[PDB]
Length: 256
Length: 256
Image (tube, rainbow over all chains, first blue to last red; front, side):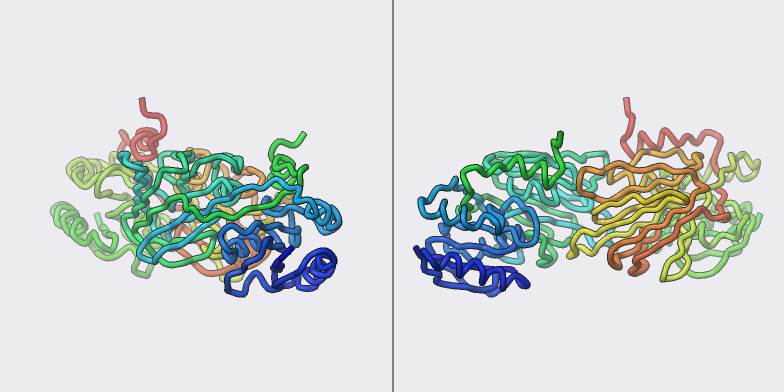
């Protein structure tokens, strides 16, 4: 089997450990930094790092290419195995014994071009800026209006990241929905809106504000159009994998 | 009476028509921007603009000098009359028909010097930055810790501005309290802490983050000490002024 391995900056030596273990049963076709630009094609990509790293690897992957993350940094939702479980991984792999999750991107269109996000996209005022009138227009519906700092549009994957910090729901990654969350609105409108993932969303602001795509500044705009992409990443999970163990351990939600 | 007039940047025109009207019975001894530098002494300061303007004007008023704000529009917490109400005001002025109100400032010491605020002080990460560890140490106690975008420390006056956008309570302006609100913390700690106005608060962040004073950005700091100042502004109100009408009208809270 043909495997690429991608690792986070200071985890190279970890990557090397994994490479040698995996080399006993499979051909490792590529080994490099999740940073380096370039398309990666393999029957499978191993990522050493965290959700951040997996995110960057997901954008490098040939559309289709299953991936697997080894927790190197901390606990996240996009990592499947710890390093002490490497032999378990080799055993699951042997028989291809995994649950496969599909995580789909969103596509963002604006004057800045076309962006892709696995978590979310954010429009927000400058720190020195006054609040802004923001118009949210779902599908063919009339508009919702907010006077706010900004708005975050999230995928199920991204529901547990920034959107959760401002009051959004925990969305299970299988849900077929998008999530819209005003940032610090007036008139106490601190509730998110959940729409079907087949609806598109136009966001307009009264003046240009900052756009962040998966948390990276990218420029200022008055207008974006967001929808579900057909691009998606595939995440391999061990059969026991339990997302709800992660909601407890990492988010601190629902502990006994 | 010897009267100074201060207007917001754009409102030179409302200032001018307030200025001609006031001069028919009184003497305008000073006429200029509320953002311009210098202490202002008079029998009365008339301020045209909004809460933002009064806020900047309160900093210029000689300890003592009573103030009265005029708003272009809908009534605000720090203004007392609308720009059509010059009739009633000059009436009240002539008869000194006023409710006298006093609001203290807070004192912020840090790396950057010593600041005054009538509303609040905010520590907050860059748009591009990760979340930060924040330590809050009230007066004598042990510390409260958050992983967050930042924290807002507010007076009763400032409770209705940025703190309320992010979950804080509405605090009536006569309460002898300070309010501490974290901005978007993890583990769902979106609740403010209310402490007596005679307690100091120290805030420490894992790295330098932005400091805003009364919504004006002031630079980067890692440590602040906040306490109640002895300084205060006095604000003249017509006897019919009701703060709760404003909570309903401007905030949107509690309409029938």
